[PDB]
Image (tube, rainbow, N blue to C red; front, side):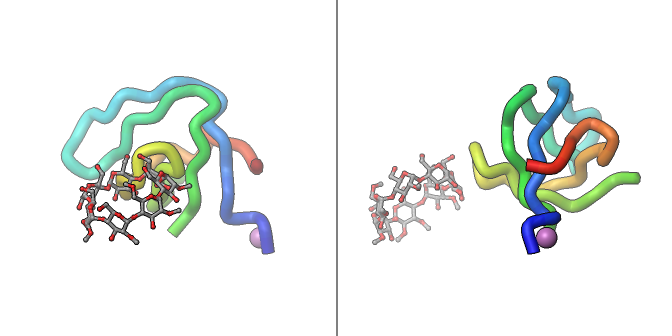
Length: 55
Ligand SMILES: COC[C@H]1O[C@@H]2O[C@H]3[C@H](O)[C@@H](OC)[C@@H](O[C@H]4[C@H](O)[C@@H](O)[C@@H](O[C@H]5[C@H](O)[C@@H](O)[C@@H](O[C@H]6[C@H](OC)[C@@H](O)[C@@H](O[C@H]7[C@H](OC)[C@@H](OC)[C@@H](O[C@H]8[C@H](O)[C@@H](OC)[C@@H](O[C@H]1[C@H](O)[C@H]2OC)O[C@@H]8CO)O[C@@H]7CO)O[C@@H]6CO)O[C@@H]5CO)O[C@@H]4CO)O[C@@H]3CO
Ligand code: NI
């Protein structure tokens, strides 16, 4: 109901073709690794869920 929007707690650099880089403070909408869309870049890929918190 609002539990699909998150904010990055830490920077993260992509390792693979399927993960998504992000910066601390970047917000992510969810579509241990979650499929997300960056609300900064619109790119969609997997993120480590422990790197983000509810926003
Ligand atoms: C450009 O100005 C016209 C535009 O102005 C208003 O849009 C605002 C928007 O409201 C505002 O949002 C709050 C912000 O937008 C930001 C996004 O919200 C944010 O997610 C991110 O956006 C990302 C996208 O998510 C990514 O997908 C990607 O987009 C690039 C596309 O990749 C898929 C790429 O194809 C290319 O887009 C083309 C587009 O191709 C699909 C093409 O469509 C025909 C054309 O878009 C038209 C559009 O159809 C038309 O709609 C009426 C209008 O759009 C206006 C909005 O209506 C208005 O909303 C209030 O004009 C567009 C331009 O003519 O052209 C596109 C551009 O080439 O390129 C995409 C950009 O790289 O990447 C982006 C960026 O990371 O960031 C957005 C801000 O950058 O700002 C908007 C204006 O900038
Ligand atoms: Ni929710």
